[PDB]
Amino acid sequence: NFCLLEVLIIVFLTVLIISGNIIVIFVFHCAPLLNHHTTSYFIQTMAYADLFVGVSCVVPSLSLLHHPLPVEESLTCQIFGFVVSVLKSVSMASLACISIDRYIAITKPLTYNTLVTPWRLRLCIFLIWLYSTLVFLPSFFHWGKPGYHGDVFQWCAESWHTDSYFTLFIVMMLYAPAALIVCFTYFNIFRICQQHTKDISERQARFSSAMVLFRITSVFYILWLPYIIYFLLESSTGHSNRFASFLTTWLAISNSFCNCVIYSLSNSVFQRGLKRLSGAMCT
Amino acid sequence: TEDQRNEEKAQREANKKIEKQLQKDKQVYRATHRLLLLGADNSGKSTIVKQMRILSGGTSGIFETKFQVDKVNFHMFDVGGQRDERRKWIQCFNDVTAIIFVVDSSDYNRLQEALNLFKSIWNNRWLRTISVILFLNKQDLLAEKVLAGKSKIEDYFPEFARYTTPEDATPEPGEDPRVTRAKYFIRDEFLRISTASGDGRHYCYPHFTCAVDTENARRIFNDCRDIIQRMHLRQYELL
Amino acid sequence: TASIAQARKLVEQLKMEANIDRIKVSKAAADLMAYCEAHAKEDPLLTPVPASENPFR
Amino acid sequence: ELDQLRQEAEQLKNQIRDARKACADATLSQITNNIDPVGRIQMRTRRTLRGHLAKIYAMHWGTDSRLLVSASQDGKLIIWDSYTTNKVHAIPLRSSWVMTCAYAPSGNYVACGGLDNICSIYNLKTREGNVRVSRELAGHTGYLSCCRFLDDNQIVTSSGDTTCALWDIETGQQTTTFTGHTGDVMSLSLAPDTRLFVSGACDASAKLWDVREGMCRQTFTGHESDINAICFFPNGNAFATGSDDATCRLFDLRADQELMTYSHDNIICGITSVSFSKSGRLLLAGYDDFNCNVWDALKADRAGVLAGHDNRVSCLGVTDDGMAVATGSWDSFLKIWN
Amino acid sequence: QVQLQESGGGLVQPGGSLRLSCAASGFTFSNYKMNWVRQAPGKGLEWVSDISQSGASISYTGSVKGRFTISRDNAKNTLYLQMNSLKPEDTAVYYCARCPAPFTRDCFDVTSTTYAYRGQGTQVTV
């Protein structure tokens, strides 16, 4: 048996995530014109983080199926929790930064290439990884579990008990910033695109006779809101659900390959290079 | 035996120094904006070039100039040294943010061929993305020409008699309704060519300028803001 | 004066190059085929190049 | 009298047409089926050359088949290494608008030129160790379309004002000027024996030029529109050109007419750059449909594609030994194929 | 070889009528956007009317808009322009101007130089 209703989901998630991330790294490391963009570097680090969380999420499937044990869940539980939580934090803050990037592109369009120095970009990437690790340090300081990610183990749910103060800290300094940033940037960019479409259609009226960031962030945050709301709910009064906790956490995990299937079905700057590379590698 | 390795080392530091220079000059090259000025010889393109030259200098072949508005580097290319044909050297202007088109509005016949030059610019395969900024110089001259009389725009343009002004900023330049009817007929005559085609990639941005004008540099500033916002939205892929 | 003399020298030169040596198209095609088949083995892009002749790959 | 000159011109053009009619009695596809094909030519990007910012208009190889220069519209003239992908020099130009670039057969000199109407010459091998400009060639009015080095002290410069001109660098002045064209002579290739060079113009007249005599030997008109690129089939007795007619064809100097044309129904855009492989079997053609193409030069059927750029292919230069081919394009990337 | 043979002309009285003919050879004639250019003596060379590839899209100079009618036979390989109500000022030399390029709408046929794809000349006076 060995949790037959979950293991198919787990293994399909692992293989899908690592496959899509290997494909997108191939695209962004082969295509020369695709490389020279700031958002391209941001998507590259998204691919790096997503590939790491995909390869790291193999070991719960191994423990489910072949049952290995370096340490008997006493430390590898929160090791896996810290790893998955930091990598999802990295992907979330990366989406926040790419939203800031093309908000700067739309709002300040002339001084755009003056503002985003690749020095500033690489410093931003380092700040994303350092910050994502540095928020989750009270997990190491024995105060609280970072979240219900990595509770597939039977020991973790019955031993760990989250702290309201620490999860309040991580909500009001990690997830609410990313949500407010993405909402603000898409609100202003949508307003500007609205008035531009209005002017275009107006001039076409006097003379007669979706968005990739919006789609990606909307999918990411539709898949992320159940986890964050039910996570803060389960730490609000110590409420206890099993099916909701597991399904919401792995739903949040599914973001990492959905980011690549968006580019696989749209945004022909990705599809053209993928088809070119597949035709070159096949023959 | 070892001099191959020494040459590999020295060549490697040479390549690193060259790439340091190239990543300096990438910022230098993207910090500035290219504007292909084009237009008829009687059209006062050189006058506005002198105006934004005062507000470096061309020597031979191309009469370049540089000007700055709010610390944004605008460097624009008056191609005047070459011959009367222009089909081949204009393919060299796709990195240009926007073509600037200057028109002597007063001289009719010298206006139909301006319309044909716009129609050739718009439908060129390598200028399909490039968005014309259109200037209409000699505003006071056209005002006098259709205010004094005896120079009938209806003769050189047969649809002006039936034409009426749709909506316009009349009262402050409101010397007469006929001058405003004529000038908006002319900009609509350009804009009908403008909006006849295009997949949203390029748009005409018409303006009116007389002889003595200073704020046309800020006009190019605001225009280029709008063109680069549009193409950044297009790279953002929302339609 | 000068233009008429230039036109006269032009039509004289075209008259001179009217009677130039003429070979038929068959011999010209044979010349191209001879040059192609003569230098056949030395062509690196035509032939499948073994990797030993560019061995730093 | 004018009518006597008109009837002499009538006799001349009837002589030309009758010579074309009686001379044409064969077709290369028709007389010999014994040609063997080339088949598939799969060319992969061995190495990608990524320094340029703006679009690339011309590249030219060295004699050693290792060094190659390429000039681009940001104002840089980079000498590349086709082995280590290393930039030996990157010369910043005075004028950004540079439509041509030529690298000396000796290897010491490289030239730029374009809309600024100066054909500047850059010396590389110097005791100081810094690249400088040798002299500025200013004898042209229209834009400089293509230039080709004869030796260290002679260069021929084609321009946009019908004038391809032979020069002399250390004098600072022209030596000869060839004026027979009608408008916009674009690309010119030198004969292997270096005594001749041909040059195609917008008139669709590709005119041979004799360097020693100074006048046009033969004129070739078989294209329907303006000509963008010309070459030499390396025998020197034949040459093929590609134009904005969306077709390309080969003329023979002795046959002095059209010989074989390479076109297809699907291709609806004109050649920007063309070049010949070393044995002259593989005609290699850039295009405006964002990819190159590869043509058999005899059987007249294409045999390979070099789709690695997503902009029009403006540059295509084979090596002297055949060990490569490098196509530049407007996406500021140079790619060496094999 | 590019060939543009023109015929039809002679003096006409004002308010008359005449036909223009432009025989072409050497290229696919159903492919290009031809024109009609004229030069009244003492003045520059000016474009009159344009016909696109199938023939549907037609534009006219704002002087000869009502009078002249332009049409072509791509099978018979000829451009035409029919004159009605000729003003005294329509005396000029008339050239049919073919585009530099096929498969496109942009076309630079006005130039004062020896433009290659423009006819030798037929004479129409009044």
Image (cartoon, rainbow, N blue to C red):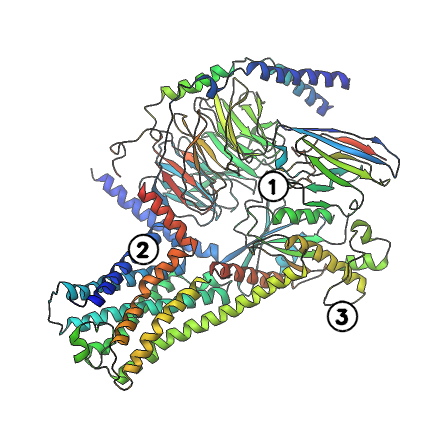
Provide the chain ID for the residue under circle 3. Answer: B
SS at circle 1: loop
Q: For marks 2 and 1, give the CA distance.
A: 43 Å
| Residue E82 in the image, given as x and y percentages of width and height | 78, 37
Give the amino acid at mark 1. Arg
Q: Residue furthest bottom?
A: A237
Provide the chain ID for the residue under circle 2. Answer: A
SS at circle 3: loop
Same chain for mark 2 and mark 1? The answer is no
Residue at 25% over, 82% down: A240
| Residue A172 in the image, given as x and y percentages of width and height | 34, 80
Instruction: Tell which of D123 and D296 is nearer to you.
Output: D296
Instruction: Tell which of B12 and D253 is nearer to you.
Output: D253
SS at circle 2: helix
Residue at 73% over, 16% down: D7
Instruction: Find residue B205 and name its label.
Output: none
- Compared with D220, B162 (above or below) is below
From the viewer's perspective, tell me whether residue A170 is left or right of residue A267: left
Instruction: Find residue B87 and name its label.
Output: 1
User: Disc 3 or disc 2, which is closer to the eye?
Assistant: 2
Q: Quadrant of residue D327?
A: top left
| Residue A175 in the image, given as x and y percentages of width and height | 34, 75
Q: Work out which quarter of the rendered image holds the N terminus of chain E and state it.
A: top right
From the viewer's perspective, tell me whether residue A70 is left or right of residue C46: left
From the viewer's perspective, tell me whether residue B88 is left or right of residue A94: right
How packed is label 1: few (under 14 Cα within 10 Å), some, or many (20 or more)? some
Same chain for mark 1 and mark 3? The answer is yes
Q: Which residue is mark 2?
A: A25
Q: Which residue is mark 3?
A: B171
Figure disc tally: 3
Provide the chain ID for the residue under circle 1. Answer: B
